[PDB]
Amino acid sequence: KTACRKHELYVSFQDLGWQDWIIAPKGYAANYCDGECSFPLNAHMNATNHAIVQTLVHLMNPEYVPKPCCAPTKLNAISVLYFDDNSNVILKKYRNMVVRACGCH
Amino acid sequence: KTACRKHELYVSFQDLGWQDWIIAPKGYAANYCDGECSFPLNAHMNATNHAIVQTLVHLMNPEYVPKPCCAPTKLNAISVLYFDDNSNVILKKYRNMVVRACGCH
Image (cartoon, rainbow over all chains, first blue to last red; front, side, top):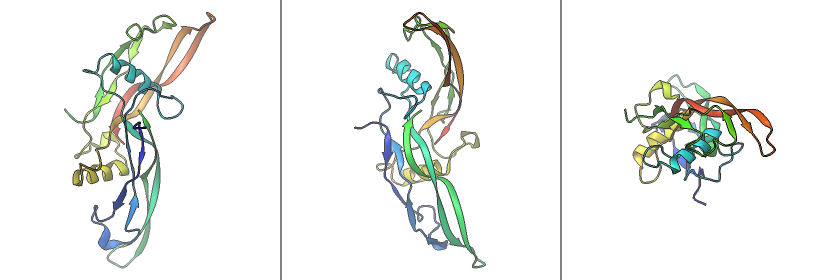
């Protein structure tokens, strides 16, 4: 299907200009949400009641209200081992870094 | 502005054709999220780390990765009084029905 789902995406820490201070990892799978949001929609799974109402209001007025959009429903963190200038090896956990599941909101 | 924000939107149950089972209310302010998600990211859009990274990665390879999507960050519930198939009068609380705030996730 071409519906709202999680897509794999690898991001190199070079994009953020962290490389010169990171030990590991040199990158990670950030992934991203993407896909069309339309019926079928489940308020207890990959959607909210509002998304159901909006999708409906959209079908009868595409020129005004847009379809809900594919966004993350579950995000994981990633730990990074890096050093500062005093040579301190540090371990920092970054939350909401990885997309695990997507849904319509 | 063209930035991600909450747009006012009243929904009438008659327009949806639901004016048969739903007794009260006759409609309610559903609102919806719309707008572009890109820098600058206003603090109110409570953008996650993942959205920040995606916005950046998108800006480097738009043909590849898309912009985060504008979606609700805070929603309210509404109670509705309706008749079911067996003519029973039910009062059901519907969560995630009213959009209060929008952000980039």
